[PDB]
Image (cartoon, coloured by chain):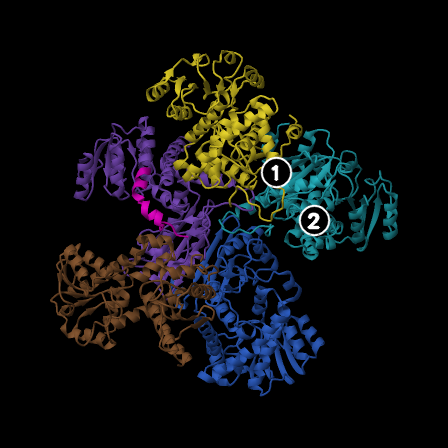
Chain colours: A yellow, B purple, C cyan, D blue, E brown
Amino acid sequence: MEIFKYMEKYDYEQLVFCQDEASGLKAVIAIHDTTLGPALGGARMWTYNAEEEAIEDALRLARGMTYKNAAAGLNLGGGKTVIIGDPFADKNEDMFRALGRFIQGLNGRYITAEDVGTTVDDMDLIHQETDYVTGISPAFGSSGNPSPVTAYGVYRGMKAAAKEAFGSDSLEGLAVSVQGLGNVAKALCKKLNTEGAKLVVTDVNKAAVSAAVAEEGADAVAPNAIYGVTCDIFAPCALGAVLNDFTIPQLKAKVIAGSADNQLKDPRHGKYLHELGIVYAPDYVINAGGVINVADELYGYNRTRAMKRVDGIYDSIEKIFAISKRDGVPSYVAADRMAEERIAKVAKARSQFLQDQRNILNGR
Amino acid sequence: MEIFKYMEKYDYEQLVFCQDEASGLKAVIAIHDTTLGPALGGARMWTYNAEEEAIEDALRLARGMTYKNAAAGLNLGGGKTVIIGDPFADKNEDMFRALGRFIQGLNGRYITAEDVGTTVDDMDLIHQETDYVTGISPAFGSSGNPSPVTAYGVYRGMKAAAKEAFGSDSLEGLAVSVQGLGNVAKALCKKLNTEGAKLVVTDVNKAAVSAAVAEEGADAVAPNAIYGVTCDIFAPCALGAVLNDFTIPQLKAKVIAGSADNQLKDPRHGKYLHELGIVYAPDYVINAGGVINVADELYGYNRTRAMKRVDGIYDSIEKIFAISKRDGVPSYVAADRMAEERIAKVAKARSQFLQDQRNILNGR
Amino acid sequence: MEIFKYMEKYDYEQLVFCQDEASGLKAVIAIHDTTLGPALGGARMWTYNAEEEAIEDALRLARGMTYKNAAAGLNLGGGKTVIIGDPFADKNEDMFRALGRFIQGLNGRYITAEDVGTTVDDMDLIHQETDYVTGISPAFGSSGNPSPVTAYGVYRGMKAAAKEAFGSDSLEGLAVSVQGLGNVAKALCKKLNTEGAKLVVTDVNKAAVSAAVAEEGADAVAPNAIYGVTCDIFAPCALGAVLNDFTIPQLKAKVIAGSADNQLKDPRHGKYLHELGIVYAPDYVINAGGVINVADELYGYNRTRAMKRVDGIYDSIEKIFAISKRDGVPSYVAADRMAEERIAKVAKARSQFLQDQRNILNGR
Amino acid sequence: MEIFKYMEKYDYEQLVFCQDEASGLKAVIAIHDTTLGPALGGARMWTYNAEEEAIEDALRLARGMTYKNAAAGLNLGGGKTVIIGDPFADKNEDMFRALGRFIQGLNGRYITAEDVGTTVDDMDLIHQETDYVTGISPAFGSSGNPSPVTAYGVYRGMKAAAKEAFGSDSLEGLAVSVQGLGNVAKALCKKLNTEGAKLVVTDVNKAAVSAAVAEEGADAVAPNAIYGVTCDIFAPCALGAVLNDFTIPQLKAKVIAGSADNQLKDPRHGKYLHELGIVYAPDYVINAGGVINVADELYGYNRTRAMKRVDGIYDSIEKIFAISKRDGVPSYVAADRMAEERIAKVAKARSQFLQDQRNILNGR
Amino acid sequence: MEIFKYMEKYDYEQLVFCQDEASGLKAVIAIHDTTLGPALGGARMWTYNAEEEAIEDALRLARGMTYKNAAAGLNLGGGKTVIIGDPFADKNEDMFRALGRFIQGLNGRYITAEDVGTTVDDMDLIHQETDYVTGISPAFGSSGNPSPVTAYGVYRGMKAAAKEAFGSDSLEGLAVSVQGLGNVAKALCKKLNTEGAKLVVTDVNKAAVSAAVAEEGADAVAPNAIYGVTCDIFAPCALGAVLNDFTIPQLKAKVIAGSADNQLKDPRHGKYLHELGIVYAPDYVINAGGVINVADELYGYNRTRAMKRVDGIYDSIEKIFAISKRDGVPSYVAADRMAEERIAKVAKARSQFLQDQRNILNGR
């Protein structure tokens, strides 16, 4: 692979390879952009095919964080850590202690968190060496179940969509398909009922269908029948790539708004959607409640404040619709634009010299 | 006595003699190892036969703390203070004020706590001169009854043992002998019932037998009949040296797991046990909940966090079994090994230069 | 190229890729080992056809600094920067400002300095963004002319060298071949002249040849027969690999001692020079007077002190010798050992916890 | 040996045993009294057959520093380090790094310096780990040559001495025996020559004898008759205990004033010298010019200031005299008193609370 | 008046006259002793006969605080502020703002509080200029009603007395006269009933008698009949000087233990009491709960901790009895002795140098 080429292509700032033979640590820290502030991104641990593959994931994921964080209204840049190994067999204390030290060695340019393959336990180990790690506060632990906060954001983003589709933000009367009944989906449903909305639902797990059904009086369909349903809104809240060539054409819904990651199988599908006239609330923006929530910890965790932050998703989605017309582009595309514009505008308007600039670190 | 010889033998770092004629202070501070962090060890006050005896106790106890703290997963070294005198007649304010100053004079290399012969009152006096003392926080005072936390750790260590012996960690159905019904034993029993375990118990004190019996429907035996009992697990939760030549051979239990200190009368007994095939969860590891609990204070006391720390005893015991096979050694021996390996591995993996390393002091 | 594989092979700490599109910055910071202290290593700027080339060089050079700094008795680790680009044509202000920022972002884990392709002007720009740069102090510039010192270093190493070969340590009488007559070489000559020694000298630069002949009654020989001459000592002070298959046999002298880098083409040669009975003073040890000089600045430059540091070369060379007849190993092999031994020994002996450890940064 | 017993007897503050197996470090730091300020005392390295020997010496020497520093008018207490080992053969880098760390770990309660067995090179290594070391400043080295100063100190003390004996304070005319002709002695002589005084001198080193004779028109006598000579003043500047049963009777002079330590073999002698009517200028007071010199460095060395501090010796000697005819006590006894009186008086008068007290550390 | 004479007599440290014409401020700050720590004393504002009178009160009151604070076990010295003026007509903002500044100007040597003639409002004004003022915390305000804490201390001191008189600390069965039914008395009564003690009581105010009577079933007597009552303990909890020539001889009680200030009309009465064999718990020691309570604020107000502090009064009174025999002196006298001894002993045992001594300021 040609690192420098990839880096210049998208103007990445840094790529950091950390190694500790003693503990078996092999990690790649990717820092794409810190224009808005320190880079924040999870640490994922996984078995990797090829070194190149690992490097590529890191790069790719850090750039994504840049976008997500910007669009979420946060004052943070995009970064990501990828640790090469079997999360089920290779972990040890020592390795997270070394990693923590390398992070401390970046002095605030990068802030980590839990992700695929790592836990709060791991984070606690990292935390013995640096404060640049989030999601470990006792305050966050007590009142910080990501779940509800994410769900709250999808909900809010949903309202903006309805308004754009239908003309109003009341979900009262609307029929909504909910694909997947996880912790998030659960809560979203709640939010929905409470509003006077009708639920159609499915999940690979029965028990899940039941709780949801019992609780909120939902109509449970089979997993494959989810797309066909005659309803107003489709909430993909499970796996990604559910929006594709088979499914798209079966869609009865006018609005797509769910918590799942990477909903589209290809950009193409994004354009398809646009051509069909289905209102799509870009996944990365709408499901951001989770990042926004860990980021509040940096200020001294306040549930209530976090929620309020999350509340801005409505405004972000709304603005996304507006950019869409402004340039006659598909939603997914506008998401990117908004992010990009935010970085550029905020930066220009912060170019004045200050001897004591203030930043999200808050002492750390 | 030949101090330097003893010191080199085991590679002690320091031996500190503190004296203040005015107050009558005579104290010995022993610091065995600080590879993992500041040395933490109680201050014991006692009447001493010979100076040499005092010195020997200090040395001996500090080395023990090194092991205990390491095996407990803490980032602390081993130290101990021995004060020569009658705890019942020789104490005065002035002496603890001088001691406190000497401690402050070690600047964080050593952290004290209450132990045999000293109280929270004494600690408060030390605390007027230094912050390197633990167990005195108002937070710790409020929600920090060592008892439950220790008991919780024995309980957890017990589960690891059962699993190793029996094949599963459910104590449901198991019969358990509980020698001693102290504050800790009390709680352990609780934990047990709540799990669906059967209790056989004894204590020199009737009242104790009664409360336990009444409360949890236990079968009370006489003190001397404790060893003979037909049960699965023996929990020595009183005095030490209960595992010996008389008792061992009477054992019906397959698992030994209690809160008492220094269970074995000799290493020999440890080997005996091994030969008999009785699963022994080394005392110092399994009863560590108490140290782990005071150590959390250093982070700003959090009961819930402490418990979670304590939870790792399960993992430590488990690992102890594994080392046992790996080297075909008795449990007691593996405990030491694990500790030792932890020190060495953690150290290697922290050898990278940092201009602002972070440590357990947390400002202090 | 398998980075993690090479890193692991020698246990490299970090590999840092820095990129700045706007400025065209492409650099690689390699940090081999920081056991003894922050990594000190020059920044070089050079043209690279393949990324891999640059990456390898960085890795390679950083590892060398580890050895050089250690052996030199310094409390610094090994690092190096490689800037990909045409020094003659590619430089700009902006690129050095960016690099300076990345370096500040490593917070003292890495200190830079001038090298191939870079000038004090470049370092000055870096200096606007960080204090982690050396060789830029006003005093340094006023009194640390590298040449003079490095020269001094080769001299002393030469004497300790005569010692083992030519019984005594006086240069008196002695006939010395001086291959290469750049600045460092001149001085070596001045020092060599002013001691009662005679010099056969060579070079590609005619002028240069004259200056020496004039200045010091030296016989100018043909650039390609220098090896051949019958001299007491051969001082390679130009290009590398001069010690190979051809020249080695062609060699007369009993001692090898010059300023050049990578004098040996292969270890093989080091190994050959050995049986031969020729006393080869290791390049990296003997020519270290310049690092040492720049390192002093870290304490507030003092030509005097610096010079005194340099003197130590003699003893170092000396020590290399003994380690040779201690394991019966080649000179070049013993340099390595002496270095690795110092690292380990010093690391063990600093394993004690301190809350306010002192380090070379001297509050930088 | 009963440590606590000896400690209590003189109220020693601390006795610190430091050990580092890897380096072979075995040292004892004794801290007698820190009432006036941090303990200042040299570090000596010497061979010891018995631990007890070393322990005793440490204790002994530290107590002496208490007296010396006090009497000298300094705001420093008394301490001393004893490193057990062969200075000629046992030294290494690692051992001094370790010791340096232990010293840093005492946080200013103890300041070190060169002594028997140690060099400025040793102190430099200590210096890499702590600022609690003296006699290593570049300026000190540039302008605080101990000899010159100590010499100066003995001189002045000599004059205040003539004063009480030989009415005036002029050295003019005066015939002086100079036992021992090392550096300090030479100077004493230079100063003594350049004042109109005549010198009968001795030594074991022939060369030395010549230098003085030449340089200053001095009569060289036999090493064993020096006591005998008819001189005005006897200046013992070599070994100790020269004042004993044999020599005392054998003595002619009216004044005793040299640089040597432990001039008296026993107090008994001090007591004897007394009735005799011989004016004995206490060793520790009169030869203190070197401590004073090294102490100045604590403020940022100033030869001038240092020198001026030294002048005070005259007055101190003077004062010792008065305290003599004030209690009708021997010279040597009055030195002690003057010291203890200063400690107490100064301590009482500084008993007022201050939140930001000033101390000699001068932010070290 | 002769200030210096009075000052030397008792060794006062300082007398500070503060003036501000603009606001009309005239204040005298008296600092008697700060051996134990900063001086703490209330600010009293009153109309003063003569300047000399004011000065005399200040002096006199500061010395008293020295004793009280020492005997209470606090690490504080004695001071007092006297402001010349009509508390009912002369106060203004400006004057307390100036005073606050002068206090800040003493930098921690003196800490103020409310007293006769000043309020929390006044303290708040002082607090805008300095932190050296106590009793104004929101925490203290919430849970800091002096009342109960003082009462708790009298209660505890009472138990020590009973034990000395009667042989046991149970007040169960005892009859107790309570002179005065203020907020403190109220609570004390409570404490008493709750213990199974019998109450005899009186107060100039009916309502008071009633509440007490109703609540705790007390026997209310007339004010003048208080002394005659046939009971075990007399608790003077109102005005002082109640112990005199008339009253003393009427006493039926064996123990005197109340909250009132300056119980004795003359020392003489103290001796009388002693001769009569009535056990007297010195007022200033026993009623100290109030000072102890404000002093806890300095640590960050903790009600529970304060109470525990207060608990030591028992121990202080107890010790007072012991000194009484030890020297065959009256109680009142021993109180003073204890205080004095505490100052002297604590000071001696804190004479060791520390570069970073810790103190009650806690940052302030």
Q: Is residue A175 left or right of residue A340?
A: left
Q: Chain of mark 1?
A: A
Labels 2, 1: front one = 1
Q: Is residue B31 left or right of residue E240?
A: right
Quarter of the picture containing the N terminus of chain B is bottom left
Label 2 residue SS: loop
User: Which of these two is toward me, D61 or D73?
Assistant: D73
Residue B226 at x, y = what percent?
Answer: 21, 37
Number of residue marks: 2
Residue type at the position of mark 2: Gly
Label 1 residue SS: helix
Circle 2 Cα neighbour tier, 10 Å, few/some/many (<14 / 14–19 / ≥20): many
Location of residue B227 by image quarter? top left
User: Which of these two is toward me, E251 or C106?
Assistant: E251
Q: Chain of mark 2?
A: C
Task: Say if E200 sits above or below D280 in the image.
Answer: above
Magenta-drawn stretch contains E258: no
Residue beneath disc 2: C135
CA gap, disc 2 and disc 1: 35 Å
Residue beneath disc 1: A347
Q: Residue furthest bottom?
A: D167
Res B56 seen here: no
Residue A302 at x, y = what percent?
Answer: 43, 39
Task: Say if E63 sits above or below B28 in the image.
Answer: below
For the residues labelled 2 and 1, say whether their Cβ atoms are less than 8 Å apart. Answer: no
Circle 1 Cα neighbour tier, 10 Å, few/some/many (<14 / 14–19 / ≥20): few
Magenta-drawn stretch contains B140: yes
Residue type at the position of mark 1: Ala
Res B75 seen here: yes
Please state the extent of the stretch shown in magenta in the rendering.
Answer: B132-153
User: Which of these two is toward me, D22 or D114?
Assistant: D114
